[PDB]
Amino acid sequence: FFAALL
Image 1 (tube, one colour):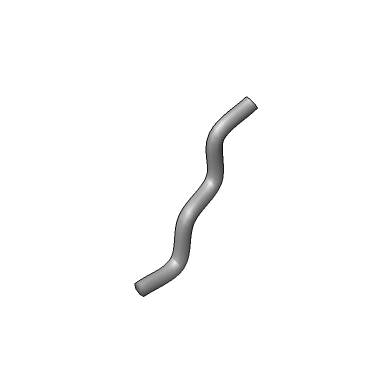
Image 2 (cartoon, one colour):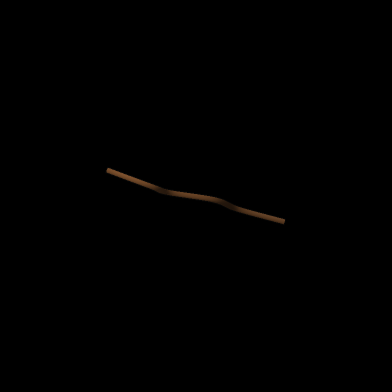
């Protein structure tokens, strides 16, 4: 699981 908000 990978989640990113930039």
